[PDB]
Amino acid sequence: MKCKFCSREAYIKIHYPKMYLCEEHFKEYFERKVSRTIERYKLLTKDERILVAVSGGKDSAVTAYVLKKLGYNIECLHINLGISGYSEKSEEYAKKQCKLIGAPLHIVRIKEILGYGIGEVKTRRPPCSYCGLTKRYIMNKFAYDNGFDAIATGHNLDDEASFLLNNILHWNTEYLAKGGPILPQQGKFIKKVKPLYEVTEREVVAYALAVGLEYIVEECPYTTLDMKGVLNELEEKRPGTKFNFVRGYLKKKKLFEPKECKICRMPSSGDICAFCKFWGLKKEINFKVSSTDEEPFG
Amino acid sequence: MKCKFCSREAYIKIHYPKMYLCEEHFKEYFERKVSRTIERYKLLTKDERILVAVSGGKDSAVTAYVLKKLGYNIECLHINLGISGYSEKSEEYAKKQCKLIGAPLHIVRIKEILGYGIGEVKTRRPPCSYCGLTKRYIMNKFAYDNGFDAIATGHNLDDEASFLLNNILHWNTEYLAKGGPILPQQGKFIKKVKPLYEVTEREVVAYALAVGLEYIVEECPYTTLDMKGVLNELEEKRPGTKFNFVRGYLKKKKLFEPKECKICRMPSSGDICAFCKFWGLKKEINFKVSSTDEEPFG
Ligand SMILES: [Zn+2]
Ligand SMILES: [Zn+2]
Ligand SMILES: [Zn+2]
Ligand SMILES: [Zn+2]
């Protein structure tokens, strides 16, 4: 097959709208779509200082890559989970990505600041579950401490769809109230946006490979995959299913709609916050930085 | 394997709770579960005159069969869809079932009273879609005209689950407000109940075969199957999924919660009702009967 817009060999078939595209015209389509998403939902403006949490996975990598190419002011943060025999390679993937992207990369090593790696704490709570708590907290407090205006994550259409299906099966109506491409700044919660909201996981894979981004497959090696497979099954039966599901969700989201921590002063239900209680912290963590390990002199 | 309660060969494995059961102890388990369901949701009382809409399918057949065995006062209604080469065999299956069950069977032939069989109307609305409208209307007006206290249908756990998943994918929040095992009597809408709410489709199949009920597979031969397959997939991955989904739904159902027809005087949004407008009816249909074709003299 040949590209819709030139004589080059097709690199990928895009379903909506229907067109075969070569590598370069696919890149352009992908970048335009992401730009369209930012515009439609008013996610970002070019004056904002944006932080991208880069796990070394494809999604956050492509996010930082495209925001950069689009001309946004982005810096990246990699949160090293402290798993011996795992996290070192992950951090290396994130570093290589940011070098390629040309974004400053800040690193927080959980094991260094908290004393323990993910999967080393004496608790029966699943490693990846307190991992999620810990990571979200650090992303936000780092963004906050350093005066960032926004955090962009790499959640794509397939992520939103699978998260939606999962939370509906479990009737997690609280989670269901808080979906969509944007969580507006609210107190010490920094604005969080999802620029890849409307691109598919398949398009993300294709984009990374097109621009020479290399990535790891699994951030925490300790369901979503079940949901994605189910949704992929349904999608092949009835193309348009995933998109239709999310669109419907955005319209009905409203139906799910019905302090400061004594340690770190970040938002807290209860007087001491979840992060602080779990980690047994008596003192605040200061994530303020004046430079990166890679550019110590500015 | 041997039965949990005797020395007979296992007929089926029940998952919740875990037990192998012979034919007779399975029948007993199934009948008890249905009885438990009626009790828990206050669906029916033994004094009520109950109508079961029997399609010739396994679900309505087992419903009428068990309500009868439990000692309820049940009569059956078969609504013949008027499909040449299809409906005759379906009606015959319903007749044989009611003979076996020992319930009076009333028959309404759509083609006789309306002039047209399902799939013969000059409309682009899917045959099975106006079939659904027509059938629900007739069931209710027949129950009403004849002074029945309740209509019992054969929807089982798998039906509720698949209907739920389908309507959530489409965000049919109106439909979502109206689920669960009971729709209380409301004006000329007769009380509708689902006694098989807590038994699985697999248990229904096993019960019919155990009691010698024969049935057709498809009422209207012109998605749910897609949903059931998906849900069966998920169930084998994580047993307990279907039940958990419905239980969660019952608890959250509340979140979806926000006349008389000029022709037939049955409930109508708009001054003329959907049934009447579709069929272009200028006159009411009187479903009052003094007897059955099989017992013309009482
Ligand atoms: Zn091209
Ligand atoms: Zn705190
Ligand atoms: Zn037995
Ligand atoms: Zn009417």
Image (tube, coloured by chain):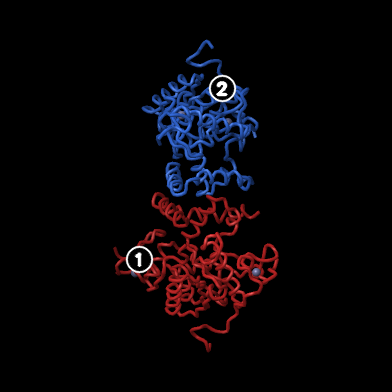
Chain colours: A blue, B red
- In the rendered image, the vertical position of residue B20 relative to residue A196, given as above or below: below
Numbered disc 1: secondary structure: strand
| Residue A11 placement: quadrant | top left
Residue B257 horizontal/vertical position (percent) = 63, 55
| Residue visible at 42% across and 52% down in the picture | B235
State the quadrant of the C terminus of chain A: top right
Residue A148 appears in which quarter of the rendering?
A: top right
Question: Mark 1, residues whose alpha carbon is within 10 Å: few (<14), some, or many (≥20)?
Answer: many
Residue B188 occupies quadrant? bottom right
Task: Establish if A100 lies above or below B74.
Answer: above
B171 to the left or right of B14 = right
Measured from the top left, where is residue B213 in percent x and y? 40, 73
| Inter-mark Cα distance, 2 to 1 | 68 Å
Query: Is residue A231 positioned above or below B34 on the image?
Result: above
Q: Which residue is mark 1?
A: B21
Q: Is mark 2 within 8 Å of ligand 1?
A: no
Whether pointer 2 and pointer 1 mark residues with C-beta atoms closer than 8 Å, the reply is: no
Q: Chain of mark 2?
A: A
Q: Are marks 2 and 1 on the same chain?
A: no
Q: Residue furthest bottom?
A: B297
Of residues B6 and A41, the one nearer the viewer is A41
Label count reads 2
Residue type at numbered disc 2: Gly
Badge 2 density bin: few <14, some 14–19, many ≥20, Cα 10 Å: few
Q: Residue B242: which numbered mark, if any?
A: none
Say what secondary structure mark 2 lies in.
Answer: loop
Mark 1: C-beta under 8 Å from nearest atom of ligand 3 = yes
Badge 1 amino acid: Leu
User: Residue B187: horizontal and vertical position, in percent?
Assistant: 67, 69
Quarter of the figure that contains the N terminus of chain A: top left
Task: Give the residue number, with chain letter if any, for mark 2.
Answer: A71
Closer to the eye: label 2 or 1: 2
